[PDB]
Length: 134
Image (cartoon, one colour):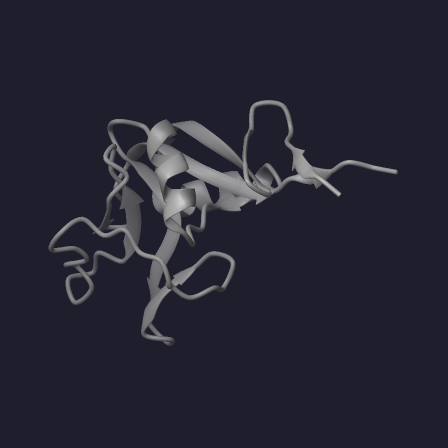
């Protein structure tokens, strides 16, 4: 009936749980780290979800679950969903023809693209919250 239960060290917002990771990681690094924890690198689909992430975001930048796929020819989230909501910094993205294929979130919450082998100090995972029983 009510789904706001999250594992130790994760934070609940709406029906989801979020892990604000800290550590030195390239994008595909953070992708597998989230998978190891039974989550996914975060997908963002509304301004309310973004505003929650901004309140907890590392000041020095974080990987999120968006990257440019060559065959589909667009940015696609790790869970296969398309970009509806977006929060690009003004002028972004600007490195698609330039090999900057992975997306990070600044301390402001705004997104920019980057080289996938860039090292950042933070990354965010999500998973679904579990629910109250009968």
